[PDB]
Length: 161
Length: 267
Ligand SMILES: [Zn+2]
Ligand SMILES: [Zn+2]
Ligand SMILES: [Zn+2]
Image (cartoon, rainbow over all chains, first blue to last red; front, side, top):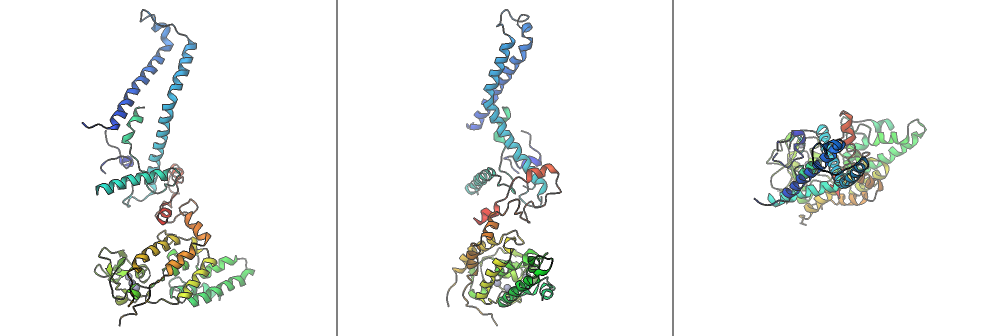
């Protein structure tokens, strides 16, 4: 994982076998992508099929333009849920990134909290509370003068999708 | 009279603002009544009644740190008037402009008024200390004045003027200033005990609590505090307040959020 440039480093959990949930979440997304590619490939063959049956294989199913329509109708429907889930998360992420950049432009880099400038239990409870407070603020646009709390390294499964 | 009361001294202050700065609350009252009469006498002019009145009370271009309603609240006594030379746990400041370097110090009120405009910093030594300012300097917080007049003047200002809406020189709305004051006094005053050096053994001030209770009854004060950090109620200081010089895309993002750090810190 090659490391991000300074205009985006603030948005990464970084330093400026056991099981894990994220392993399994990621590998299922990896596996999902394969099937989507294969479906696309088969849809890719349809125009040439009246040649790529008989010139290639002893026997195969006859099919027609009307059937291609209905297949395509069916395929689109089955993707809508995952599409909505992808889109909504991506928009939310891009918004948080662009806002953090605009604030980095308008703010003062002399301040120790500027994105370009920047204990156990209590620091951890600090991290968690900063996160919960940033979450509650963000819902109503009550977040005008501090960086949104975010990490992108969890989002590997939306990257695959 | 209008000219004499709108004329500014060598520090920018009208006679009214001077009466407040000097704790001459009955004189401030006398002038403030008179200033209302004067503004109400010149209603025949092409100016609005208010412009004249604001000119005499708190003139345009006044540094916010000198706005009278704020100054009246800052006018408390030095802790030494009630602690004497006893050591109590309180906040303390060094003042380098005055040679009050890190072994020495003054209490919060001296730092706010006796050392206004100096290099002063919040000190890191133990809080169990009295305040050296009455001994090392010409300390202006030793005199209480007339308490009943101080309170009467506050009531009048709150109904006479829109000054409640201004933030101070650190972006603190007046209410956020008062409530921090009460919270601080609550700890300091619980250490008080009944019994060439200045008059000690006085009773501690309850003005901040009385002032907080009265201000909280004013709709304008309350609305002005709760709407703080809205796009209309633009915080002048430390708060992304200059934006027009950035390219338009970053403005359309950065206008959309709104602030609550101070409203949350108050609540
Ligand atoms: Zn003092
Ligand atoms: Zn003093
Ligand atoms: Zn000083």
